[PDB]
Image (cartoon, rainbow, N blue to C red):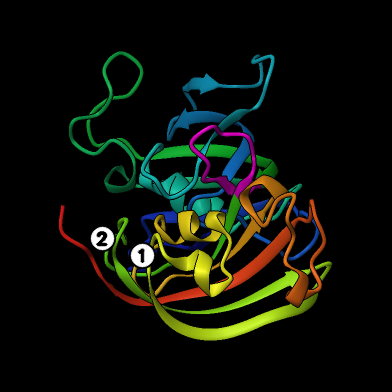
Amino acid sequence: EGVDISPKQDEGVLKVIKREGTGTEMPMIGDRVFVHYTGWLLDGTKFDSSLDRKDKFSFDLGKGEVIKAWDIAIATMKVGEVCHITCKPEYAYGSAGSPPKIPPNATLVFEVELFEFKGEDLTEEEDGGIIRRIQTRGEGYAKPNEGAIVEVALEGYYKDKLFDQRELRFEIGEGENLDLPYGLERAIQRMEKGEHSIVYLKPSYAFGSVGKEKFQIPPNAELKYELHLKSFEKAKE
């Protein structure tokens, strides 16, 4: 008796909100999410729960790190929200099932509480220096490499004041001479054609100790960019 939230609307994932969450944001593909859950077969046989865990269960959303029904359901949740989802085998473990605990072709029921979620860290050192919040996923899978000619539309903010708004075509590895910070170039390298995202850059992945005088940006400034990767051509290697 829940609401069907399957894309195909094939009743593959039904959801009933037990407690409403707060705010209006919902995690998006790539965001790191934190939840507590309990899973049961349709007859009531409990086969797993994280409620004993010293810490919440976390994974990156929409990266297939969990069954389909989960990537689907959690993207429809708000922080604080508690819901129950019944998932058909197609969105769970299908025919193959999952040994001991879950038989072939089993419909599953999960109780899920979303505690928190945050943007994806794109830095190689995982130091939180470049955080992305995807607004609209692109569609292509391929990404620009060093040397690629990319076409982007961007808006850069410092303390929410807009300081740069341009549409430009440029070569990854040459953005510096066009007043783009290295970290933005690094972030573009992780985007797909058509992607619309907001990227948060700490000083060391921005203009760092130098700042950018003509944009009224001082040394050690954090920056936020909202951008669109329109198209690109990869370079040879």
The secondary structure that dominates the magenta segment is loop
Identify residue type, mark 1: Glu
Compare residues 185 and 79 and report the one nearer the observer.
185
Q: Magenta span has 153?
A: no
In-image side of 226 versus 90 (left or right): right
In the displayed orientation, state which residue is furthest to the left: 236
| Labels 1 and 2 touching (C-beta < 8 A) | yes
In-image side of 109 versus 96 (left or right): right
In the picture of the structure, the residue carrying the numbered disc 1 is 192
Residue 80 visible in the picture: yes
Q: Which residue is drawn at 54% across and 32% down?
A: 125
Please state the extent of the stretch shown in magenta in the rendering. 118-130
Residue 82 visible in the picture: no
Categorize mark 2 by other alpha carbons within 10 Å: few (<14), some (14-19), many (20+): few
In the picture of the structure, the residue carrying the numbered disc 2 is 142
Q: Is residue 76 above or below residue 18?
A: below
Q: Position of residue 80 (x, y in %)?
A: 76, 47
Q: In this view, does 151 lie above or below 207?
A: below
Q: Is residue 176 above or below residue 59?
A: below
Categorize mark 1 by other alpha carbons within 10 Å: few (<14), some (14-19), many (20+): many
| Secondary element at image label 1 | loop
Q: Which residue is drawn at 29% across and 65% down?
A: 148
Identify residue type, mark 2: Ala
